[PDB]
Image (cartoon, rainbow, N blue to C red):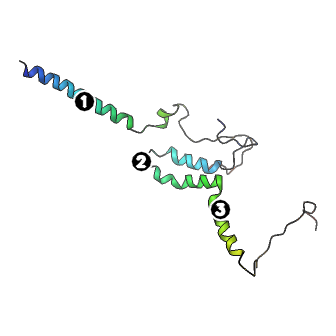
């Protein structure tokens, strides 16, 4: 009756250990430009300076 | 921002190298960034002309030591009074 109630607590603590190791993995994982920077306007391509612009200026 | 806006409101001098570098960086995630090292190099010496200054010093070191100097189609210098004279 007491071995089962200790195995329950050990399972509940190993669950927290797995959760902690997971939530540590999750932060060091790299992340998208749409999640790290603003979601709308998801491309990093600037295309900036649009009045006196030259054709051939893109690459 | 004013990321690539020039003095006339157009694109700046190194806009195209920067936009190529950002085209690089858009389709890559990290762990895979070592391949867009050349574009960045192309951008940086677009900015500062380090490798062209090195190359032109290497060629000027050789033309200083020639007694012959230049056997070439030469380049003329004019006064500003005489751009279309003859």
Q: Quick one: quadrant of the C terminus of chain B? A: bottom right
- Crowdedness near tag 3: few (<14), some (14–19) or many (≥20) residues, C-alpha within 10 Å: few
**Which of the 4 image quadrants contains residue B85?**
bottom right
Q: Nearer the viewer, residue A56 or B19?
A: B19
* SS type, badge 1: helix
Q: Is residue B81 left or right of residue B2?
A: right
Q: Give coordinates of residue B51: x percent, y percent.
A: 62, 61
Q: Give coordinates of residue B45: x percent, y percent.
A: 62, 55
Q: Nearer the viewer, mark 2 or mark 1?
A: 1
**Which of the 4 image quadrants contains residue A20?**
top left
Query: Which numbered dot is residue B52?
Result: 3
- Crowdedness near tag 1: few (<14), some (14–19) or many (≥20) residues, C-alpha within 10 Å: few
Query: Which numbered dot is residue A17?
Result: 1
* SS type, badge 2: loop
The subunit carrying tag 1 is A
CB within 8 Å, label 1 to label 3: no
Q: Residue at x 75, y 78 (%)?
A: B69
Q: Give coordinates of residue A10: x percent, y percent.
A: 16, 25
Q: Give coordinates of residue B21: x percent, y percent.
A: 56, 49
For marks 2 and 3 on the same chain, the one whose residue lies earlier in the sequence? 2
Q: Nearer the viewer, residue A19 or B86?
A: A19
Which residue was labeled with disc 2? B31
Q: Residue at x 72, y 48 (%)?
A: A54
Gap between marks 1 and 3, in whole Å? 57 Å
Q: Residue at x 52, y 48 (%)?
A: B24
Q: Is residue B59 left or right of residue B74?
A: left
* SS type, badge 3: helix
């Amino acid at each position: 009756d007491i071995l089962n109630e200790e195995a329950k607590i050990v399972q509940a603590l190993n669950n927290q250990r797995e959760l902690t190791i997971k939530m540590h993995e999750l932060k060091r994982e790299e992340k998208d430009y749409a999640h790290s920077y603003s979601p709308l306007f998801s491309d990093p391509v600037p295309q900036g300076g649009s009045i006196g612009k030259a054709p051939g200026s893109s690459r | 921002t004013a990321a690539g806006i020039s003095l006339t409101g157009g694109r700046n001098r190194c806009f195209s190298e920067w936009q190529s570098f950002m085209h690089c960086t858009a389709k890559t995630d990290a762990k895979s960034r070592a391949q867009c090292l050349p574009n960045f190099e192309d951008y940086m010496e677009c900015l500062h002309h380090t490798k062209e200054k090195a190359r032109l010093r290497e060629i000027e070191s050789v033309l200083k030591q020639k007694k012959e100097g230049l056997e070439a189609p030469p380049v003329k210098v004019i006064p500003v009074k005489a751009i279309g004279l003859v």
